Each structure stands twice: as structure tokens, then as C-alpha cells.
Length: 48
Image (tube, rainbow, N blue to C red; front, side, top):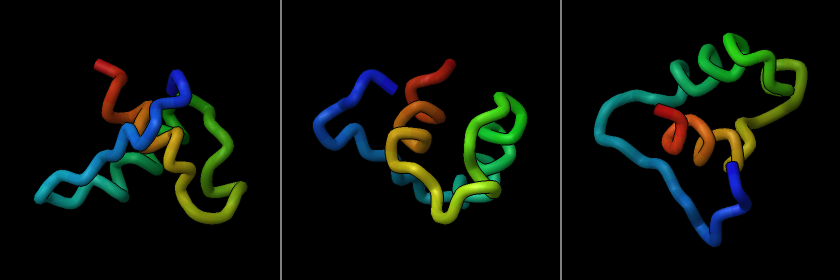
């Protein structure tokens, strides 16, 4: 989201699966696209 200069998103708990599901939940282009977009990770973290 936004286009943050290294927004990052690393929690010491597994978030990667949830990022993908949250992405799917929002209808983002993940799973249909390879990897997880860092911008999507950032979006996941920014999205409250």
C-alpha cells in the first residue's frame, strides 16, 4: 500500500499464510501470481 520505502512486515509468528488468505479475501492478485508482493505484505500490515 502507498508505495512505502521499505514498509516491511516481519512478525515473529507466521503471517505469510494469512497474508495470502487476506489477499485472497480482498481479491488481490496473489496465488494467481507467484510470490507474495511486498506491497501486499505492506498492505496487510497497514490494513487495520
